[PDB]
Amino acid sequence: ANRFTSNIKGLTQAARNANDGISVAQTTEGALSEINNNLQRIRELTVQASTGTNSDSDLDSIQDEIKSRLDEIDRVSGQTQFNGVNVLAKDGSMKIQVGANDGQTITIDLKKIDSDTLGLNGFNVNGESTSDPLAALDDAISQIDKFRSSLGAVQNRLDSAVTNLNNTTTNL
Amino acid sequence: AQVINTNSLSLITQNNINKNQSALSSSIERLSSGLRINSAKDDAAGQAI
Amino acid sequence: AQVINTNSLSLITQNNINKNQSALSSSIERLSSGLRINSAKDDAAGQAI
Amino acid sequence: SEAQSRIQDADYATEVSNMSKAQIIQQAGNSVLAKANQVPQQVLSLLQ
Amino acid sequence: SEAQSRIQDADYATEVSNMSKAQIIQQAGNSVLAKANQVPQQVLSLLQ
Amino acid sequence: SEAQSRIQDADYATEVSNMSKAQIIQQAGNSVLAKANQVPQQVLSLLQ
């Protein structure tokens, strides 16, 4: 009976840790979605900028707005944090302890995401300009899309772990 | 009666309610906004597409 | 039930309503005037042109 | 745009029904949890 | 906000059952305490 | 005018939820206060 009670308490603590992780993942996912919106906004107006009808003076304003968006992306990347921990500051790993026994943890992976990491870091449209702005931006967006896919997968895994732990604790 | 220290039946009922909780929350959250994906707890490939 | 202090579900509902209201205000102000650009926080280059 | 419409759309017809089912389940669960809590008072009656 | 809700929340679903169970055990304990105070009365018959 | 409105805006959506939560907490507190007053009653039966 004492062993069973200890097991139940450990499983409850593991469920609480799983809740901590399930919140961390959704916060980071929302941050990256808000970042991706900026990439899309960059996409449409760099598409219009590539057209030769717009004069030289136009490209300066376009590049100014582009630089504003890039700086906003870098700022949102640096700022976002959870409980004194900067999620996007450095590429790293966080392990959520979801097992009462020692060593049973589920890994959460985070990769550093700044303006340089996604690519360009030197994006100019008024000249020399980037050799291929458009596919480079598409490649950048695909990376955040895969990142959201991974966070959704780990989100589902933590949800399943929580429900499994609840059933196990009730049976015990 | 047989169990006086522990209400295991209450635990079963609470588990059923908790199981319904996620469905209710997801349903109302998806109802509030137009998007079905809604910050994809749902299928990731569809969200990427 | 578990939601007691922070009605998180209705809270995300209210969050969605604000994102709706932003687009509603933009649409109504663009419809009221004949100018789509409307003091270009949207398309600065097009407005200069 | 028509292609995008299929992938993400609320489809309120299913959502309202699902919300109704979930509400009924939650209310029923709370109601039966009430009777579950009311069950164990026969212990006190047995004593006296 | 929804994150701190997990750390800080009353969760009446588990609390009301704990309250009811504690009350039942309390009344049972007081009843058995009265029946226990009834116990030492048999000495009087022995004395007389 | 919009500047003034931003500083002082009602935005009924949040306050209606807050007030509803307020009467929910109030009524729950009164309900539990009833049982709180009920708690010391059994001492009378403990007496005899």
Image (tube, coloured by chain):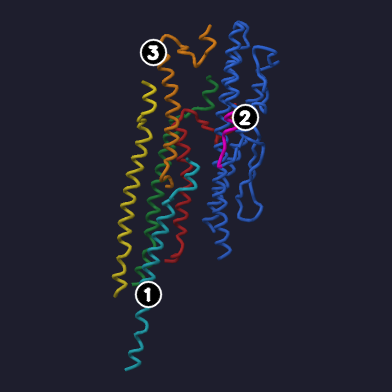
Chain colours: A blue, B red, C orange, D green, E cyan, F yellow
Question: Relative to E5, is C32 on the left or the right?
Answer: left
Report the Cα–Cα distance between label 1 and label 3. 81 Å
Task: Tell me the subunit letter for badge 3.
Answer: C
The quarter of the displayed image where residue F1 is located = top left
From this viewpoint, which residue is outermost toward the bottom? E48
Is E43 drawn above or below residue A38 in the view shown? below
Q: Position of residue A20 (x, y in %)?
A: 55, 45
Tag 3 secondary structure: helix
Image mark for residue A144: 2
Q: Chain of mark 1?
A: E
Decide if residue A61 is on the left or right side of residue B33. right
Q: Which residues are magenta?
A: A75-83
Residue neighbourhood size for the residue with mark 2, other residues' Cα within 10 Å, grouped as few (<14), some (14–19), many (≥20): many
Whether pointer 1 and pointer 2 mark residues with C-beta atoms closer than 8 Å, the reply is no
In the image, A135 versus A159, the foreground residue is A135
Q: Position of residue F24 (x, y in %)?
A: 34, 45
What residue is disc 3 on? Answer: C32
**Which residue is disc 1 drawn over?**
E33
Image point 45% across, 22% down: which residue? C23
Discs 2 and 3 lie in a common subunit: no
Q: Hey, what amino acid is under mark 2?
A: Ile
Which quadrant would residue A47 be assigned to in this image?
Answer: top right
The type of residue carrying mark 1 is Leu
Task: Give the CA distance from mark 2 to mark 3.
Answer: 38 Å
**How far from the left and from the top, in percent, is residue F21?**
36, 42
How packed mark 1 is, by other alpha carbons closer than 10 Å (few <14, some 14-19, many 20 or more), is few
